[PDB]
Structure formats: C-alpha cells, structure tokens
Amino acid sequence: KETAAAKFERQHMDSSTSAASSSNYCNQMMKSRNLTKDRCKPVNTFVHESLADVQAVCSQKNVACKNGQTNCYQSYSTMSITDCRETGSSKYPNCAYKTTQANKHIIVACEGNPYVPVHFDASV
Image (cartoon, rainbow, N blue to C red; front, side):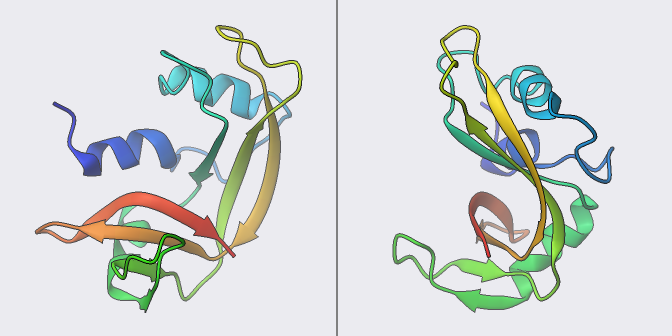
C-alpha cells in the first residue's frame, strides 16, 4: 500500500507552482491528487516549497500537535501555502472548493527512519 510519507506528498506537496494562480486551483488539485475519489475531503492544505525544505521541518521546533501528540514540528520560516475549503455548492462527486493563498508557518507530524512528515497538522 501507499506509505504514509508518500500519501503526505500526494495530499500536501505542490513544488511545481509558487502559489495558487486562480480560484480554480483547489478544484483542480483536489481532483487530480485523488482526494475526492471516495468523498469530498472538506479541508486540505498544499505547500508550495521544495520537498527537502518541508522534510527539514522534522528537525525544527518540536511542538504538541492539536490532538496532544508530541511528534509535531513547526517550521522556523513561513512557507507558501494554499488552503482549500469545501463550499456550500459542493456535492459529491462534484466537489467544490474555495482557494485561499497564504504565507504561514506549518506544523507537521513526523514518523519513521528517515524521519519524515506524515500528517499536516496546522498552519499558524
């Protein structure tokens, strides 16, 4: 099966663009990354940075995750992110999202060896 690390890349990484360029970014990306296959995932965040810079966050500031776990890490720097949130007209299989572009610190949970991001916790 797909590894947790691979799933994080699929769900959260977009190193191919620097920022969302149009209001349709989330509709396109949620569909193309197969996040709407079974149901409309209600919220998702894409990170517009190199995979290496995001993996490096697992060696930065240790913080508690929202759910209390202590394998979360906050990035020292802000990063380019896109927030995707389901709209009121969203109806499976035609899932619909609002695109919001922002520059925030990210918080990820890390696991494994190599120690890599496997869950996106929050942006602050």
